[PDB]
Amino acid sequence: IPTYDIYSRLLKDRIIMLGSQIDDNVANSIVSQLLFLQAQDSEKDIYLYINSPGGSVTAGFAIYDTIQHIKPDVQTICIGMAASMGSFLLAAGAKGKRFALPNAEVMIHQPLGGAQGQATEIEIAANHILKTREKLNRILSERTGQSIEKIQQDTDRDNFLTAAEAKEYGLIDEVMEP
Amino acid sequence: IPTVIEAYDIYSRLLKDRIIMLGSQIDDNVANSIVSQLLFLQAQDSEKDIYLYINSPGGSVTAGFAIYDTIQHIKPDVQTICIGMAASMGSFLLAAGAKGKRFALPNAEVMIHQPLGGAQGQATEIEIAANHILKTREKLNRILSERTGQSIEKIQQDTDRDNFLTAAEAKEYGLIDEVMEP
Amino acid sequence: IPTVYDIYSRLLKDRIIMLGSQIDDNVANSIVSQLLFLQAQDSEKDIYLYINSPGGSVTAGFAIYDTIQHIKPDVQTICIGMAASMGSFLLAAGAKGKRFALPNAEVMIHQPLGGAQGQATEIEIAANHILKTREKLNRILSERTGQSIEKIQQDTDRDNFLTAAEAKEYGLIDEVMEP
Amino acid sequence: IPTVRAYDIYSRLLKDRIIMLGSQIDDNVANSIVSQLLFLQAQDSEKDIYLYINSPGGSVTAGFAIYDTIQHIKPDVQTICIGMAASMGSFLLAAGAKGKRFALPNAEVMIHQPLGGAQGQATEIEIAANHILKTREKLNRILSERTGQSIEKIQQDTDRDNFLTAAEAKEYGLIDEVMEP
Amino acid sequence: IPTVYDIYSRLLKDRIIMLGSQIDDNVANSIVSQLLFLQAQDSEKDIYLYINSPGGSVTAGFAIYDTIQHIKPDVQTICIGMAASMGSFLLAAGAKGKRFALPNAEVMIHQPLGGAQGQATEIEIAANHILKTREKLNRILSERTGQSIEKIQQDTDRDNFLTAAEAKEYGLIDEVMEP
Amino acid sequence: LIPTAYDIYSRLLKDRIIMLGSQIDDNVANSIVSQLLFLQAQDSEKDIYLYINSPGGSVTAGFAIYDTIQHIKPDVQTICIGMAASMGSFLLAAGAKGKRFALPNAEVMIHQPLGGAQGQATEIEIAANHILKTREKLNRILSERTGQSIEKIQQDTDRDNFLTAAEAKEYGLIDEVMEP
Amino acid sequence: IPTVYDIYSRLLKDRIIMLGSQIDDNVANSIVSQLLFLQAQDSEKDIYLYINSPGGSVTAGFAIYDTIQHIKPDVQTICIGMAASMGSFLLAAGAKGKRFALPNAEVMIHQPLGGAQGQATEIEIAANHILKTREKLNRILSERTGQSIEKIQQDTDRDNFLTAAEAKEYGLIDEVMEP
Amino acid sequence: IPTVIAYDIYSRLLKDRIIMLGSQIDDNVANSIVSQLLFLQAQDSEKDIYLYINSPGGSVTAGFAIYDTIQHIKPDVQTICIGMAASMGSFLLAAGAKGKRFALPNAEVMIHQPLGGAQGQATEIEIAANHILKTREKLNRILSERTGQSIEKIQQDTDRDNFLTAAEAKEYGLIDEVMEP
Amino acid sequence: IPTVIAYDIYSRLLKDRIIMLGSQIDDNVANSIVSQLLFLQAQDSEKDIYLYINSPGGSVTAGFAIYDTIQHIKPDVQTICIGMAASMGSFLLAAGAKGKRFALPNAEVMIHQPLGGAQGQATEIEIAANHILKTREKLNRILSERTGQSIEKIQQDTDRDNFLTAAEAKEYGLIDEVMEP
Amino acid sequence: IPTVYDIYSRLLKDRIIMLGSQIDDNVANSIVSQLLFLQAQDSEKDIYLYINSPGGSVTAGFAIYDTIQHIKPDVQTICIGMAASMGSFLLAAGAKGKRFALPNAEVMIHQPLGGAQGQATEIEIAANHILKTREKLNRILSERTGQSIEKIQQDTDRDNFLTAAEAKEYGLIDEVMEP
Amino acid sequence: IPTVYDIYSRLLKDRIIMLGSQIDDNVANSIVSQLLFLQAQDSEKDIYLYINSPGGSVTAGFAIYDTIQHIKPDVQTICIGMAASMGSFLLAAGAKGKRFALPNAEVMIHQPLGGAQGQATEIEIAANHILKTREKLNRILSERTGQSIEKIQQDTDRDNFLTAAEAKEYGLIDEVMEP
């Protein structure tokens, strides 16, 4: 990472690069970048590049809620792949400012997790992850215009979409052309 | 494991006298052996009692139900005798012996608790697993209710956490019929 | 972690502390030092503590908790992502009226976890100590939420997940911070 | 394990109603010892049985499977300590028929409180602590009955590892006689 | 570890030292050097030692202990979170009248731990050494707490957890620091 | 199993010969005790022969063998081949008086007991007192069986002390070097 | 390790060298370089070597030992916590009259440790070498304490723990440093 | 390991007074070999015994248990090297009855000094060194007696690994004859 | 490994003077093969023995224990390669009685120079190098005698892995006949 | 593995050999010995070789194959479950007209697998060898199925799964054994 | 490693290079670079190479050796602690009359170590190469000590430990550096 690295130079121009799995460390850093950019200028757009296989749903919601909280628009730009929570964040960008490059891929599926121990503990974990899926699907419905029933069906298995398909689905607004 | 010459290992020698020893965790291999022994004893004599000693921390619920159903399926009464400890599916099998012929020795310990499991993967896979283990707990509790005389609701409450019982407490609960005194 | 100052050090300049990890003695040492430094800079201005944490060490969390209550500035707490176990205890520890969660943040409360090994009398000592620790946590959660101790005991017996709105109803936070 | 029809040496001794407890006690060992006790009773409910004990102890519940079977069966079970009887091993030594509990002169006996573990939620640690304390009370009460010592004395004497010579074990009431050459 | 100086170096500028880890030779070397440095800068002004520690090496602790007693400034000790074993020994070693704990901080005292392996005579040497080390710890604790050596022996036979208020009654601290 | 299943050791046991050729642990001690009891049951008057090639091992396991030897009626000859070290040399010295042997190039080693202790100071104290008492017990018996003073045994066992067969006879650990 | 310079660098400005670890080649390299640097800055002013060390490599220790005797400044030695094995050898190596221990610091002396593997003639070479090294260590210790080599041999056969007062009586240090 | 009707192949050969050493020498192997030698003398104290040796060597004390038993018993023990006899294996080859030590033509013999290890305090390393040096003196003295070579030549010739052909072992005096087809 | 009534299958073949070498060659395998050869000679010193070989080779010294025993005993030993005979395996294949060395048509033969290792001081590496070089000369000389190929040719043909069909092994002189159906 | 013999031994009495595992030298040695024994018992009666095998060593497979072709009795081959790689080669090697599969048995053919490591010239030798081995396998498969060598080469470039009916149609077996 | 520059950089300013580790390609690269830099700064003034090293790679040692001989400044060598194997070779390589050891430093000489695995011919190549390397080392050692090659061969057959005074008498150094 070349140098005050290349990411800090892009941050000076209100660009945040997500290029990894989403965990609490990544979310803490991105949230802090978003807050800092709003403090610098509450009006100018922010640009969030997303190449991510997804990761923690709660870490992803830290980023998601910060995006919706701050005053500047956050443009989202998918490069390479936005899968799982990554495609949720892609769809979370400012309306009209969600993009994917022509060969970028988008994948949606249901959340993953685990449960171990007593029957009642497994029941609690199952209820929690099912409620988490409902929350994701409700928001994806609002952000895409698709019905919750259709999102439920379309995420039962791994669902790969081209950029053109992601646009038609309502996950992005435009395929960014050269 | 000593040998007895009339050449039997000690467990085979006791099987000759219609005694089956359960002294390990319950898995499919152990259940396969126990079931085969029960079927063999029935084939030998369908009237004489069988004696099942139980010192077991429990284990696989489905393997325990292979044993449970075989006990109920065969014609001879299967006396159960707890020595040391009968916990989880082990206490379930202890309570499954022929009515009036379920025993524990005075310092044997009985422990009841809800079944354990796990689930990994997609939310809908976790839901299927949760629904399955919950249905399995209902099945266990319903049978325990029948065999002890306790209501299902009391069993649910009394198995939420590990519940250790003395032999005397096990008799009062209905899990055994008598403490076998010296 | 980009440079502007690394990003966290830049936010600290504006009296913002980020808790975004498991709570251990190292994290608590750092958070406590930041709180003391900010009080030294200005004893009157608010401090903002963002919390995204699965929890962790009870004693480390109480190092942070007691420092929050000790210092003069109000400490606002803001849950983003998840505040679980000791993290949710710290969320509820913010200045009354200044405890927040964002709309999709999750809150989870549950009894403390631990272990005990050795002689019977050593297991007894360890059990008494963790039981006392839970009573201590529940007493404070009762005063900070308005709920009875009996209700907190019962509601923490197993993992209990709360939405942001449920956390407000419960008294763990004061407001869901809307966009 | 040499052979002596063919017997291993332990099977040969079992023909003379001798059982050798020469290892840590777990469920596998207890299962074998119990089966040997039941077999010998089935062969002859009158004749004494001889239980040699060289054991560091082990599982308390497995030890009680052995303990209760000894008390259940009709024959007297003599106990003979060689080398070491520690923890649950010393509990079983004291469990022999009264008047027929022995140690050889240099055998070592050790008594101490039970050991265990617990992990997880506070309430789970509470349940495990209550269970091991009740197990200790059960062990101390029986040891009081078999030794003549008060439960309060047994409690104080098992708080830490307590090593006894054979002659001290006799004075304590854990055995009846030191078998002198 | 945020930057302002890193946060700990910034606190050191105000004569605050943070012990927030297990005690070992490296930690003691750092703490001793900070104490000698602070005395060199000003031999009259108080030093503040925050303690959140599970304890650790007895000899490393005594490097710290003897340096506190050696230097001219008073060293205040402030327990946050937990001071256990050699950590609670150092808490009680602060200047008399200037030993503190925050209300929910926990203090634990117990006898030293160690090991030995090899020949009978090697084990005997190691046993005699740790027993003498325990006598030394107990004698000093007795002096610093006002409790008899026999009571300290009894009270440290097993893990002994104390609240901050109990630590004050015991004589391990002078006051519970209230908000 | 080595050659015939009825192995070579079982064939030697028919002739009242017990072959110790390993470290001494509870399994080995239980086997040897059982063999000794068996041989006494077969004939309480005929000698037993115990060959010893052992680096030593568990002190309590060794005392199970030692006390059984003293308990039974038959004389137990001891014959050192290769090495009898630590508790192996203790058992070598415990054979019937006048019937303790070593072959000419066999080696004997004596030293103090080994052990460990971990935990609280008072737990280490208990463990140290126990191993010190075990050493006094070993030295007292070795004094009785060799004729050497307890103080000399203490000195001579402070460190590993290797002895030739002839030196072990001079020391009193054996009665005769068995020459061809 | 806080910044002021790191804390050790800051103490080095005042001619203080902190030994707070095992002695190996890397540690010896650093301490020798610090000694040479301090001589080059001022050949007259005393140097201060603090020692909390469990010992370590004999040859690395002699790199430090010989450099102390080589340079012109006096090197005071101050034991804090523990000086064991080669650590106690270095403590005894300070300028005569300027060897100190703090009151609860401990000192341990014993013979060197090592290993040998391979052919009989290789084990013989290794045995002769460690025996000659012990003779070298005991001879120098005899000169530095005033004790006979026979007494030092007897007193290092096994681990031999000494209090600070005992180390003064032994001649390993000159004074116990009281507060 | 095949069976001959029931003997395993080695037990079948032992019936004909043949003992096969085909492994490293440790206490277990020595226990077996010593027991076989004692057994064969008990059957017949006059007829020769045949010890085939293919061994890389191993424990010196285990080798001396075998060595001393060979010299103790009345029957002659012929030794026959096949494959390799190295270190303590070549010591045992040379220990066979005079005139009855053999190697097949392509068997190898290797002699060298004993190997060992030592850890701990200087005085413990000294004790370990003195013991292995004394052991080497014992081995060389006996090899001198059995080969006819001086002790000083044995010392020189075993300082490093020294490989000999069958014919060279005969000229050296380690064996009496190369057994030709 | 199935049983025939009671023989395991290998023991049943041994009854018919058939030895199966079906694994890597080490001291344990050579100990068993040698014992079987000696046993069969004792049963009948005139009747042929049949040694099947499916082996990747292995220890050169273990292989020479088998080799020399084959040449020492009176019966002819026929050798029959099935599957593969590589390295010391192909050396033993060529060691069969002249005219009675066979391979089945799809069996594979591979010859190559010996493998080993050396570690330590320069003079120790030199000793190990000299020894493995002398071993290679020994192997090459015997292979020259048994195949009719010059030593120079065997040297160059074994510098690297050299794979031979059964037909090529016959032309090379490693076997006498390809055993056709 | 039950008794009555073990179950495989009881079937061998009836001239049935079960191959139900990977083909390695141990398996091949046993199967070759079983074939030779059965020929010695009766040189005229058929032998039955059941095959459920994922393949294995090519040379081990050829020990079996050559022994099948060498002995006088016919060897029927019967595929149950799966015959893959060297397993399908042995299936095709049965006596002509006496090679079978059960209706849901699967057959798989592909090219041999191997590895090579070292100098360029060593890699070249290993490549030439495995390429020659494939030519041998294909030539025999061509003879035993009636397919051209070119077709066999094409059809084994990748894993090629075949139903029992496709295997019969291919020439690898003669009949699908129907219930 | 304290700051002043780390301590080694501070000494390099005064033309001092410290070797205090095993010799590998990484250490040799750094030392060679320092030697070349120092010559470029000043081709006339002496360079001082301190050596405490157990040795290591022969080729890496020759990288240093040849660079010492190549550059114009005299390189003094000073053994502290131990110089063994290639370390003692480099000690003996210093400028004539400027090779030193401190009084208790030890010097060890022995033959090179290595290994070889694979075909007979590969083992032969490796043996020939290490024997040649030993001849190369012994030839240069003979030139630099004045001892004959045959004596060096004898004296390096096994590990040979020398005191500083013995190393001077041998010709490996010129002077024992006294205080």
Image: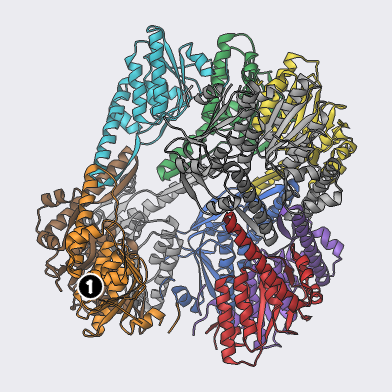
Chain colours: B red, D purple, E yellow, F blue, G green, I brown, J orange, K cyan
The residue labelled by disc 1 is J67
Count the numbered circles shown: 1
Image vertical order of residue F99 relative to residue G134, above or below: below
Image vertical order of residue B120 relative to residue K167, above or below: below
Image vertical order of residue G73 relative to residue I45, above or below: above
**Is residue I46 or residue K149 the one in the foreground?**
I46
Residue K27 visible to an observer of this rendering: yes
Which quadrant of the figure contains the N terminus of chain E? top right
User: Could you say which quadrant of the image residue D125 lies in?
Assistant: bottom right
**Is residue G69 or residue K95 the one in the foreground?**
K95
Say what amino acid the circle numbered 1 marks.
Answer: Thr
Position of F166 compared to I82: left or right? right
User: Could you say which quadrant of the image residue E130 lies in?
Assistant: top right
Residue I95 visible to an observer of this rendering: no
Image vertical order of residue F71 relative to residue E175, above or below: below
Position in image of residue G74 (x %, y %)? 63, 14
Position in image of residue D129 (x %, y %)? 77, 58
Which quadrant of the figure contains the C terminus of chain E? top right
Residue shown at the point (42%, 26%) measured from the top left? K27
Where disc 1 sits, the SS reads helix
Residue shown at the point (18%, 71%) measured from the top left? I78
Position in image of residue K160 (x %, y %)? 40, 32
* Label 1: chain letter: J
User: Could you say which quadrant of the image residue I121 lies in?
Assistant: top left
Mark 1: give few (<14), some (14-19) or many (20+) Cα within 10 Å: many
Position of I24 compared to K56: left or right? left
Position in image of residue E154 (x %, y %)? 84, 46
Residue shown at the point (60%, 12%) measured from the top left? G73
